[PDB]
Picture (cartoon, rainbow, N blue to C red):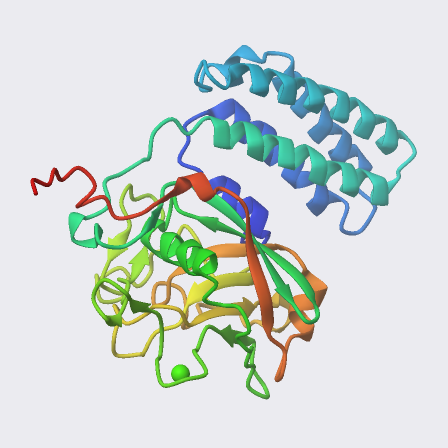
Length: 334
Ligand SMILES: [Ca+2]
């Protein structure tokens, strides 16, 4: 009764306001729930007919797309219409495997359309963090390990300071050669500890550890909560927009007693519903999730002692990374 697909969490975290595209999204999302037992084909066909009816009125979606991007979005709508027909044909033969494969392609198109609706960064990051790199949008990072590639999407719309720090460190090569750790009986896979005396990244402008604030956007808020756990904000019951209950959620480690003590140590949470008890965990609202694994699920589960990151690549979204601009408009006189 909770959303556990990281791609879906990321779609819902897009700061958009368009009810039709959300209905289209929900109808296509529902297909996987209906097909988990491979029995409820009527509900699948109802989902596809609803999706088709929404696509029949593209203007109700395109009205939220800025005029610069409307024509790419029209191509995506056309691809969705073609794909829905393809899936309706597959549903007629009750081909669960192909319906699910095509459903993922359709939802990727929905994601692309939804992301094109973000017009302008949704809030002002506190100026006290203007000395830190910030990701004003999404980025996709491919992490090459000795066991294969992990692809993560990091969400600067929900965690611009945290995602910005990560993309900046990736670009600096900080993670190259760093080992993974996973305690014996643990669902937490960690990396980002320099093998040396430092605990994180040293800011070359200051000569000191580049600490980042705790940054957690609570459901329904416009601005992230900075520097305080949701519990300490009096909001223990409120959930993050980017919650922990997805396999491969990527978050910042920090000392338990230092909310603003993170820098480079990160962890993946290998969430498993089957083994997770009913009730809240000790992670949501306390540690900042800033992205999700979207490819490499089987690889992630096998990472352990001795494994390491060989390299990390910014696949998409580098242009969303904003370096500190405080001294960028200063005029010198010699
Ligand atoms: Ca160290």
